[PDB]
Amino acid sequence: AMRLPDGTLQVMVEARARAQVTDYIPGPYLRARGEVFSEIFPIDEAVVRVLVEELKEAFEKYVANHKSLRLD
Amino acid sequence: AMRLPDGTLQVMVEARARAQVTDYIPGPYLRARGEVFSEIFPIDEAVVRVLVEELKEAFEKYVANHKSLRLD
Image (cartoon, rainbow over all chains, first blue to last red; front, side, top):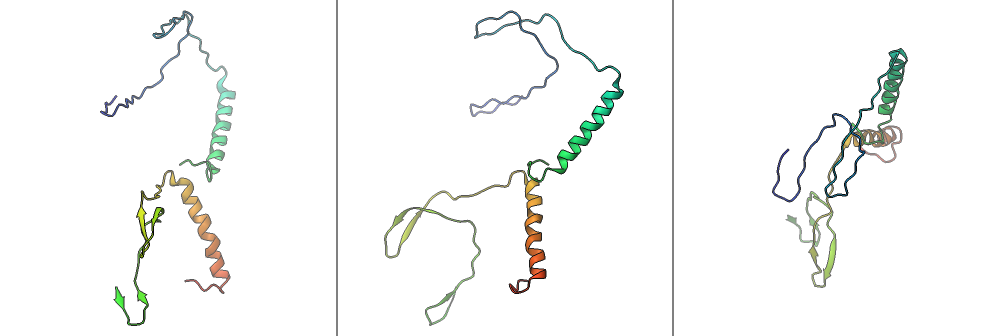
């Protein structure tokens, strides 16, 4: 984080995990707590790899259409 | 500035940017009160790079084929 003497405070953040909200407090301030973590992983990743190849093909095709999408 | 006694002036120029007039002051001579210039900046020139060649070929193949305009 870097500070600037102009009334605008800019800070960069990175996402690491998720959280759940069950208890709610009328803010300000707002306070909650998570109960369980919900996450799943792919199974039999051969089809997942085929889908990844198709997604890469789609991304490559989209790159070839960057003549008007304004992207590097 | 190089002059002749014939009422005609030859001056070489190099334009910087277009200038507009908001309030006109009658003369003679007619004087104009300038304001902030209407300037632009290039952002995300990736599309501009393709546009440059697309615009270039249109007259590059024209002057080469059609010669009545007689451009260099």
